[PDB]
Length: 232
Image 1 (cartoon, rainbow, N blue to C red):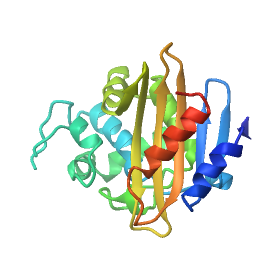
Image 2: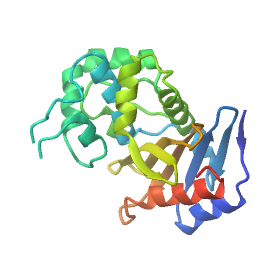
Image 3: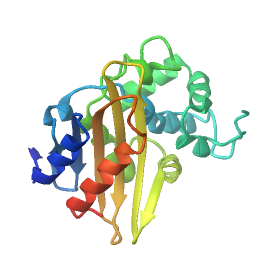
Image 4: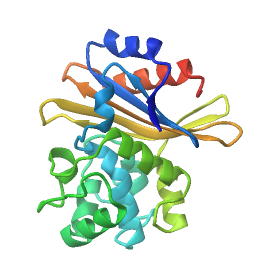
């Protein structure tokens, strides 16, 4: 039920960037694999800031913050901080949750290897928490469908923080991640497309990064691939 898709064109997209990558697509029926390094789909990597999705769910569910709270620096909300790079709001939230509640929630959700270690404010960037791209697409598909074991309102509020782009009636939700301080570097873009008729198609892009690459390379590869697959 996890099968290589029609991959002759998308494979070349990753080759052209001179790196190894996979794109996992989950529909209501199938999981398909694309890219030039399909073994990445079942390989565990640190989640990097893709973990912000679960951090926000845990923090909101346990009333450690709310969507209107202003975090002092600009000063900003949890939702404003979701899409921003190198902001400490999510480290502060992790400290409020605390190691014990964070580990209990991550174990209850079963996210990746579900190991957070002893440092509550960085385990998603350097380990020991790791997750495969297949696990990430399954997690984000559950979020999109309001099927995670959290409040419906909490799931809706986190989904609203994840809107990336809208065009031509399609909404693209998701979250970037880049673990730059481990070797090799790991890049993520995990999320879903809400098509005009309401159908949901979830994705997880995972690729090796290098320091000279523009951050936009992940979105660039994602959009070209989703177009080739007629998902947008």
